[PDB]
Amino acid sequence: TKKVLIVEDNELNMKLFHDLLEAQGYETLQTREGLSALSIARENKPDLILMDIQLPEISGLEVTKWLKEDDDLAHIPVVAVTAFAMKGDEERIREGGCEAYISKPISVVHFLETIKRLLERQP
Protein backbone atom coordinates (compact mmCIF):
# COMPACT_ATOMS: atom_id res chain seq x y z
CA THR A 1 0.00 0.00 0.00
CA LYS A 2 1.22 3.54 -0.68
CA LYS A 3 2.62 5.17 2.46
CA VAL A 4 2.81 8.77 3.66
CA LEU A 5 5.45 9.74 6.22
CA ILE A 6 4.04 12.41 8.54
CA VAL A 7 6.55 14.63 10.37
CA GLU A 8 4.55 16.50 13.01
CA ASP A 9 5.24 17.32 16.67
CA ASN A 10 1.63 18.25 17.52
CA GLU A 11 -0.53 15.32 18.67
CA LEU A 12 -3.82 16.82 17.45
CA ASN A 13 -2.41 17.66 14.01
CA MET A 14 -0.82 14.20 13.71
CA LYS A 15 -4.19 12.62 14.49
CA LEU A 16 -6.05 14.74 11.94
CA PHE A 17 -3.52 13.92 9.24
CA HIS A 18 -3.54 10.22 10.06
CA ASP A 19 -7.33 9.97 10.10
CA LEU A 20 -7.71 11.81 6.79
CA LEU A 21 -5.08 9.71 5.02
CA GLU A 22 -6.34 6.43 6.49
CA ALA A 23 -9.81 7.26 5.16
CA GLN A 24 -8.38 7.50 1.65
CA GLY A 25 -6.85 4.04 2.05
CA TYR A 26 -3.25 5.10 2.66
CA GLU A 27 -0.88 3.72 5.28
CA THR A 28 1.15 6.13 7.40
CA LEU A 29 4.56 6.31 9.05
CA GLN A 30 4.74 8.78 11.93
CA THR A 31 7.40 10.77 13.76
CA ARG A 32 7.68 14.04 15.68
CA GLU A 33 11.27 14.90 14.73
CA GLY A 34 13.15 15.89 11.59
CA LEU A 35 16.23 13.70 12.01
CA SER A 36 14.06 10.67 12.72
CA ALA A 37 12.09 11.44 9.56
CA LEU A 38 15.25 11.07 7.50
CA SER A 39 15.93 7.69 9.10
CA ILE A 40 12.41 6.45 8.39
CA ALA A 41 12.53 7.79 4.82
CA ARG A 42 15.60 5.70 3.94
CA GLU A 43 14.46 2.51 5.66
CA ASN A 44 10.73 2.50 4.89
CA LYS A 45 10.78 4.34 1.55
CA PRO A 46 7.52 6.34 1.81
CA ASP A 47 5.72 7.55 -1.32
CA LEU A 48 5.25 11.05 0.04
CA ILE A 49 6.46 13.11 3.00
CA LEU A 50 4.17 15.55 4.86
CA MET A 51 6.56 17.82 6.75
CA ASP A 52 5.57 20.48 9.26
CA ILE A 53 7.99 23.38 8.78
CA GLN A 54 7.71 24.64 12.35
CA LEU A 55 9.14 21.71 14.33
CA PRO A 56 10.37 22.58 17.86
CA GLU A 57 13.96 21.53 17.22
CA ILE A 58 14.63 22.33 13.56
CA SER A 59 13.18 24.07 10.51
CA GLY A 60 11.40 21.61 8.23
CA LEU A 61 13.12 23.36 5.33
CA GLU A 62 16.55 22.25 6.54
CA VAL A 63 15.30 18.67 6.74
CA THR A 64 13.91 18.99 3.21
CA LYS A 65 17.32 20.22 2.04
CA TRP A 66 18.94 17.05 3.41
CA LEU A 67 16.27 14.99 1.64
CA LYS A 68 16.93 16.68 -1.71
CA GLU A 69 20.71 16.40 -1.37
CA ASP A 70 20.45 12.62 -1.04
CA ASP A 71 19.88 10.89 -4.38
CA ASP A 72 18.17 7.96 -2.65
CA LEU A 73 15.46 10.23 -1.21
CA ALA A 74 15.30 13.22 -3.56
CA HIS A 75 12.56 11.69 -5.72
CA ILE A 76 10.05 11.65 -2.85
CA PRO A 77 7.58 14.54 -3.03
CA VAL A 78 7.60 16.72 0.08
CA VAL A 79 4.46 18.61 1.08
CA ALA A 80 5.08 21.39 3.59
CA VAL A 81 2.66 22.19 6.41
CA THR A 82 3.15 25.76 7.63
CA ALA A 83 1.68 28.49 9.80
CA PHE A 84 3.00 31.18 7.45
CA ALA A 85 1.59 31.12 3.93
CA MET A 86 1.84 34.65 2.56
CA LYS A 87 3.02 34.99 -1.05
CA GLY A 88 6.58 35.37 0.21
CA ASP A 89 6.40 32.13 2.19
CA GLU A 90 4.92 30.22 -0.74
CA GLU A 91 7.92 31.20 -2.84
CA ARG A 92 10.47 30.35 -0.14
CA ILE A 93 8.88 26.92 0.27
CA ARG A 94 9.03 26.23 -3.48
CA GLU A 95 12.68 27.29 -3.58
CA GLY A 96 13.27 24.95 -0.65
CA GLY A 97 12.28 21.95 -2.72
CA CYS A 98 8.74 21.35 -1.48
CA GLU A 99 6.35 20.08 -4.18
CA ALA A 100 3.35 21.67 -2.45
CA TYR A 101 2.24 23.26 0.81
CA ILE A 102 -0.65 23.20 3.26
CA SER A 103 -1.30 26.37 5.25
CA LYS A 104 -2.83 26.55 8.73
CA PRO A 105 -5.70 26.50 9.47
CA ILE A 106 -5.78 23.38 7.31
CA SER A 107 -8.21 23.16 4.40
CA VAL A 108 -8.90 19.42 4.43
CA VAL A 109 -10.23 19.23 0.88
CA HIS A 110 -7.17 21.06 -0.51
CA PHE A 111 -4.99 18.77 1.61
CA LEU A 112 -6.58 15.59 0.25
CA GLU A 113 -6.72 16.87 -3.33
CA THR A 114 -3.01 17.70 -3.17
CA ILE A 115 -1.82 14.43 -1.66
CA LYS A 116 -4.01 12.32 -3.97
CA ARG A 117 -2.71 14.20 -7.02
CA LEU A 118 0.93 13.64 -6.09
CA LEU A 119 0.48 10.02 -4.99
CA GLU A 120 -1.61 8.79 -7.91
CA ARG A 121 -0.47 10.76 -10.97
CA GLN A 122 1.37 8.46 -13.36
CA PRO A 123 5.02 9.17 -14.25
Image (cartoon, rainbow, N blue to C red):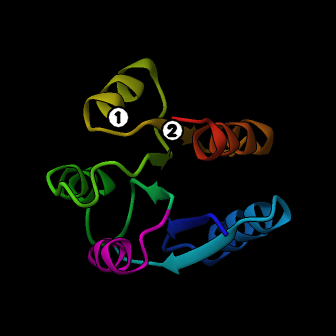
| Residue 70 in the figure: left or right of residue 89 | left
Nearer-the-camera pick, 15 or 42: 42
User: In this picture, which residue range is highlighted in magenta?
Assistant: 34-46
Q: Is residue 67 above or below residue 7?
A: above
Task: Give SS at disc 1.
Answer: helix
Q: Main secondary structure of the magenta part?
A: helix
Q: Are marks 2 and 1 in contact (CB under 8 Å)?
A: yes
Tally of numbered tags: 2
Residue 60 position within the rendered picture, expressed as x and y whole percent measured from the top left: 32, 56
Q: Amino acid at mark 1?
A: Ile
Task: Give SS at disc 2.
Answer: strand
Q: Amino acid at mark 2?
A: Tyr
| Residue 112 in the figure: left or right of residue 84 | right
Q: Is residue 110 above or below residue 23?
A: above
- Residue 22 among those drawn in magenta: no
Which residue is tagged 2? 101
Which residue is tagged 1? 93
Residue 91 position within the rendered picture, expressed as x and y whole percent measured from the top left: 34, 23
Nearer-the-camera pick, 116 or 86: 116
| Residue 93 in the figure: left or right of residue 10 | left
Question: Which tag, 2 or 1, sits closer to the chain's start?
Answer: 1
Instruction: Residue at 35%, 81% (x, y): give it.
Output: 43
C-alpha span from label 2 to label 1: 8 Å
- Residue 44 among those drawn in magenta: yes
Badge 1 density bin: few <14, some 14–19, many ≥20, Cα 10 Å: many
Asked where in the image residue 25 lies, by quadrant, the reply is bottom right
